[PDB]
Amino acid sequence: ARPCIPKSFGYSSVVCVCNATYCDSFDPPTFPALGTFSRYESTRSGRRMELSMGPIQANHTGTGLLLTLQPEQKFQKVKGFGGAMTDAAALNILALSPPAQNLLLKSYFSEEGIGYNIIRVPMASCDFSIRTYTYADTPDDFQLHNFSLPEEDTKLKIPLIHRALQLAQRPVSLLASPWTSPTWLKTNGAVNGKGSLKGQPGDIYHQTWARYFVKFLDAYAEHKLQFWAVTAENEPSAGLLSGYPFQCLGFTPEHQRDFIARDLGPTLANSTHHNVRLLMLDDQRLLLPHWAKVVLTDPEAAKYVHGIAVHWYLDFLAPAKATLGETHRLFPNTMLFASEACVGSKFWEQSVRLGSWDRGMQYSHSIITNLLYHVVGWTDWNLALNPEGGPNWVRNFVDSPIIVDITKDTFYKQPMFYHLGHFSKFIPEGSQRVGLVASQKNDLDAVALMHPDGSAVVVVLNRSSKDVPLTIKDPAVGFLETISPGYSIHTYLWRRQ
Ligand SMILES: *[C@@H]1O[C@H](CO)[C@@H](O[C@@H]2O[C@H](CO)[C@@H](O[C@@H]3O[C@H](CO[C@H]4O[C@H](CO)[C@@H](O)[C@H](O)[C@@H]4O)[C@@H](O)[C@H](O)[C@@H]3O)[C@H](O)[C@H]2NC(C)=O)[C@H](O)[C@H]1NC(C)=O
Ligand SMILES: *[C@@H]1O[C@H](CO)[C@@H](O)[C@H](O)[C@H]1NC(C)=O
Ligand SMILES: *[C@@H]1O[C@H](CO)[C@@H](O)[C@H](O)[C@H]1NC(C)=O
Ligand SMILES: *[C@H]1C=C[C@@H](O)[C@H](O)[C@H]1O
Ligand code: NA
Image (cartoon, rainbow, N blue to C red; front, side):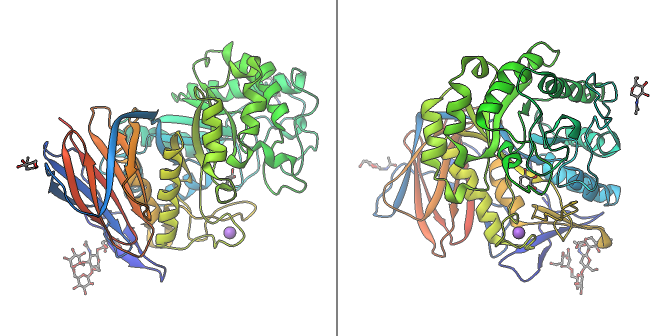
């Protein structure tokens, strides 16, 4: 409905500029009439989900690339897409004037925006906090009598989550993850560094830590928020590393198996929160399938585990077939879910690169590859950061699809926002990945989904410089004659009857 106000910061593409009075917006998604397809196009040159429509043809002839829909070939159901309400994201959003805040929240959560349906919520402090704290910092409080939510939750994160839910037309799923326990439960007595829970699963330290999850869910429930899922720990492999710089809590896969079986599973199952899902791993996919084998081959752990959460940071070293593919083969009834991604965290990446088309392409390439290897959802990290990629108490600055500029009461929507939106806007919860096969070797990344109503959604990313003329065949409906420009992403929609 309202176009991008483009601005260049000297990188490969533009950001869209928003402020207290103006922000670019979309129409709520619709399917066009049977016999017609919709195309949403974003380009490096500056197009941002531009809508065009075309006819579906009964016949096709020629030697060009054909992508053939296999609609009766069914894969995974989609849970959804979203991002993380870190302390840093909440501070950046609340630093904007209230009208600018509302336009930022609408960008993510409204059907005039990109229709997010997942929010990941840290359990107390992480690196994307300005303060180090847990919910139970009073020493040796095994009863957790002094468990309480500080203002980071009650004043910042919880009220913003309520505002997001009010804007969302889709049901929103909250996902909780802890970085560190209270230091008095830890071998090293520090939020960071190499350190695990004291003792062993089934003991007072592990039972106290499991009860901390219930007290967290109780306190958010007093604030009228319910969780879809929790993870067993953010990046449990991190707390095994000498000198780890920020909040962590080390588990080997054996330690996670026994903690789930003895402490966390039984404690959640015997609580009012028994319907909250438990996701294991919440770490790099390089740890698969080994971690899944260690946990899920123990029936006493397996009965509590709903799914396996993965982070993208070693995907470049960890081929999808050998990790996700092999994990799905061995454990086809345990869903895979991508719970954290961001650009800028690696030694060779600058924190923030305003308007980077490359970083948008990284997001869409990741989402397509994950959907092609059975993953049911994909979750960004910080919803918003400042232009330094913070704040962050260890200055571990990264990039975000929205960058706030508080001086100018402005925020910038980057290519990453539009690349995520090509999926989140058009793929409701309960959509199913279906087959789509290419007639010849090609440089495109593509994925097909069947919308809950039976209609087709196809996303096509061209990470090459070369325009690729392309036909899509739906054997029931006909042929879509189209073109994939160099450095473009398209979403196609069409009804099937
Ligand atoms: C919040 O963001 C708004 C959108 O950026 C800001 O409004 C913009 O402010 C600038 C400065 O006054 C205006 O720029 C001038 O624009 C005209 C040409 O205008 C038209 O074409 C542009 C570009 O295609 C289009 O966006 C407009 O709709 C106009 O039809 C030039 O002749 C001037 O030399 C100068 O460049 C923009 O017109 C204006 N944009 C809009 C959409 O209103 C607003 O100032 C910001 N608010 C705050 C508080 O900072
Ligand atoms: C498509 O091909 C068939 C079979 O050769 C032909 O008879 C028909 O006229 C063509 N066009 C249609 C069905 O619109
Ligand atoms: C912890 O809670 C108990 C019981 O309600 C209270 O008596 C005590 O003063 C609290 N301690 C701190 C440090 O807040
Ligand atoms: C995911 C990547 C970077 C960190 O900011 C975050 O804490 C980690 O879990
Ligand atoms: Na970096």
